Image (tube, coloured by chain):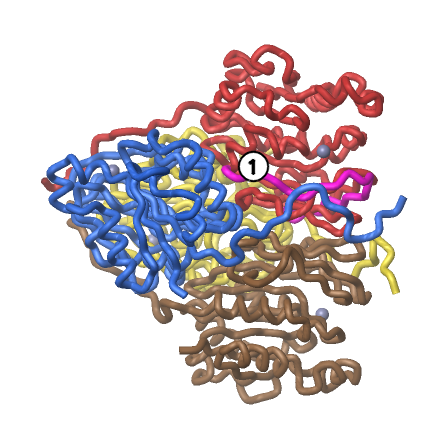
Chain colours: A blue, B red, C brown, D yellow
Amino acid sequence: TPIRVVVWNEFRHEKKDEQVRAIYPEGMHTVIASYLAEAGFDAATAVLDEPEHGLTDEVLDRCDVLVWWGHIAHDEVKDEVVERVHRRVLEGMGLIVLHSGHFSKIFKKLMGTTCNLKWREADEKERLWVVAPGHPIVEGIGPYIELEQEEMYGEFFDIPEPDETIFISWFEGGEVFRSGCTFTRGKGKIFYFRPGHETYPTYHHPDVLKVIANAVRWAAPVNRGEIVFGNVKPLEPIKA
Amino acid sequence: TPIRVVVWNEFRHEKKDEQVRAIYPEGMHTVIASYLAEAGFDAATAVLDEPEHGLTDEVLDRCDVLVWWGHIAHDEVKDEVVERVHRRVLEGMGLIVLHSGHFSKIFKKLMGTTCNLKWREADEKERLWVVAPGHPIVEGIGPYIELEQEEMYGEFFDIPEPDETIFISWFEGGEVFRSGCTFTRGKGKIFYFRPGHETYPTYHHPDVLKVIANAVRWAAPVNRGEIVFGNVKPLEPIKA
Amino acid sequence: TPIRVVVWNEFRHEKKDEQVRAIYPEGMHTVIASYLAEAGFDAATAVLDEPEHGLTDEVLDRCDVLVWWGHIAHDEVKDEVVERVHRRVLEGMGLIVLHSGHFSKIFKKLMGTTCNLKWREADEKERLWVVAPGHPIVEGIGPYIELEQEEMYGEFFDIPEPDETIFISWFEGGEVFRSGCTFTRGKGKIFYFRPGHETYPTYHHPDVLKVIANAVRWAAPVNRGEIVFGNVKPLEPIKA
Amino acid sequence: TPIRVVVWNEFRHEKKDEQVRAIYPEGMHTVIASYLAEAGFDAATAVLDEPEHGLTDEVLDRCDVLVWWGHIAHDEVKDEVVERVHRRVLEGMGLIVLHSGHFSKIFKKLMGTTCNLKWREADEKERLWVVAPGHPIVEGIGPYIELEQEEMYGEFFDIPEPDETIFISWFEGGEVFRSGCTFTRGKGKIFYFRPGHETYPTYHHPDVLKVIANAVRWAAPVNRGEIVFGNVKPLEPIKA
Ligand SMILES: [Zn+2]
Ligand SMILES: [Zn+2]
Ligand SMILES: [Zn+2]
Ligand SMILES: [Zn+2]
């Protein structure tokens, strides 16, 4: 049965910023979710200004993978919902965090670090080099993805060392970035993917959308729900 | 020149349980700090009931490596202080988390997971096998450390995958545990080391103490201090 | 298209030893391949005492995942064949190494270490604890797999640190072992799975066969073939 | 006791090419070893055209860390010597592989991959960004090292995923590289460090030499010696 994916987007820039609305008139979430649906996923969206930011228990309980984009309103996501999502990831829900989502409460909580970085908005070139060429996330991608204009993020990226580094970006201005990183938290699989500044049509680039689709598939839950913790009796005789 | 170490202990059990007090009449912190002093470290102690839990900015700014044990009052450590310690580890302070410190606010914050596990107090044998035989933390340690009595902890331990697993424990009752794990968070080096239940003389065991001393040296800051993040000018010209 | 898997087995013990033949009268390869065929894989088998050990170019070129079991005749696998296999794994072919396969020429070549370990044949109990509970390899597996009789292998196991540790074994006799380990080499995915001594019906255990099937699915290539190396022209202008 | 380091260098280019001899008149090994002696190490050199290539059992037994640079005569290192070195690394001798040492027999043997990569000799700028800012290898190193001219190596670099990535290089021509990588093999610690082309004064750069010195200290053996393997008696009773 199709993997069920919820694409969550702060959905502030596209309402109010002319240059962004021109690129994403129905929001970045609509673009990503449309692509995913046309790729066979059961795709829905959620935004910050819906009740419970669209992430009710009912929604999350039928969500296999959550995709997250935020930027200027990270602080408005309520702690109750962050905790709810955190619990679901640890139980096995997948999480794909995009671009400025590195500063989301949920990603910072999972990482345990500041998730800070260097950055510059200069309409500069990015080339995302594949460094895990057999990884399912890079199926169909070529040796790199090139973006003619993006916002630079630069090392040092204050994240725990990834389980795997999939992409490393080169930027025109001299920096590099670990731009595709996987992590596992509990049963959940997380993929950080750097591209997607709101003022560039990055989410219309077919290789970008394909990485996201590939990542949704890679992140799907396997044994969602079942771990026993706590006080336990012995499985073998203990000798006095 | 000597590495400065603060040994933090909740110090509630040793006052409320006579069986504990008999083993550690001046608390576990005193035993650990005394050994570290004799090993050549500049060692101090701090406990929960001191003001700021003993961890003022003044104390933390002169602390190279913090050692942490807690159990029954993890909740009483104020968030302001957890946040202060978290900042210090990211800037390069070392952290050694011991035994029940797996449920400390600070370790859970740095891990991003629940750090739950299975457990049992049945005075059973533990054998900590070395699985990183060339690691500095196991200098002078044989193939395993054997403790005649300890509290079992058992996988699955809900932690991010370690940078390195140093020890894996075998318990008499059937369980195993990744009982010595290293992580890096920011510039800080963390070592989780399982043994140390308050009802057993585990911190009188010479190999246990040697591991802690080896870990204090390993975890000593390099390049300690603020990392530069934020908006930056290009090092190469960007075609406009 | 179903995944094409070749199950390679030394196939000496099952002819030499009456007690082994009684358990695996047509070889362990036949039992594993039959299960895989029932699970929907396009399964074939190959054995040491065949021209090219059954691993001709034509066979390997259509092999998506190779499963390897050997023990008493690792030396007899011709270097030309080991090299052929090694090239295929780096191009993306999956490799599942079973039990005494740890000392196969192919596994040692891919690892770079001796792959030696401690061992004991004493019909003792082994409990394989899952330590990556979200990993695809453990789909359908409970917290542990228990085998009533197996040969002990024990740490230190001289392997490079795995990409992920999936299983850690507890043995009745006191030892532990990293019993399911993943590695990536080139584009190829490798899984080492410890259980499988010839004198015990381990490959009739449903959980064991399930893990192998899950690992074959996991290890199948999705970007298969030649990577570009060598001298390359610049993508950006270089100032003279 | 100072750490004993042997700097091994093929030493063909500096004898045959006047452009190279002008930069390194007494060989690249001399320059590195002289720095290391001033940094307090007990340093010695060895070269290809000495008996046993300078790497007798006697020499290797008193070597704590071996540094290796080769390029046009990797094939002339005798397999007997490669094997000797390999055994010593597994027992805990450190190994620092420099630049075209990526294609040395010893590095390839420890890695289990081809170690191939993309490359270009175009006198282009390289900026080595630190991505493990607390690591001992980068003590005293700024956010990056910049080399005005170097040979480009580019991803994909066919190595096993490093234990840690210390540096990632940006090159003027558009590529990136994992340019400082640690690995553990047996007891031995290995650091690959990219810079070092023979036609550029790279080993006269203070930060490059500092990194090497730091890596020599980091790679010093602990618990050096034969690991015990083989058949072992049980530590606990095994039931009939
Ligand atoms: Zn942005
Ligand atoms: Zn306890
Ligand atoms: Zn066997
Ligand atoms: Zn070169």
**Quarter of the rendered image showing ligand 1:** top left
Tell me if residue C37 is in the magenta stretch. Answer: no
Q: Chain of mark 1?
A: D
Which residue appears farthest toward the right when viewing the image? A240
Which part of the image, by quadrant, shows the N terminus of chain A?
Answer: bottom left
Element at badge 1?
strand
Q: Is residue D232 visible?
A: yes
- Give above or below for B151 relative to C165: above
- Give above or below for B149 relative to A210: above
Horizontally, residue D39 falls left or right of residue A202, namely right
Name the residue rendered at 39%, 34% in the picture. A105
CA neighbours of label 1 inside 10 A, class few (<14), some (14 to 19), many (20+): some
Tell me if residue B125 is in the magenta stretch. Answer: yes
Residue C141 on image: x %, y %: 60, 61
Residues drawn in magenta:
B112-133
- Hey, what amino acid is under mark 1? Asp
Q: Which residue is mark 1?
A: D42
Instruction: Choose top left, top right, bottom left or bottom right for residue B140.
Output: top right
Instruction: Choose top left, top right, bottom left or bottom right for residue C50.
Output: bottom right
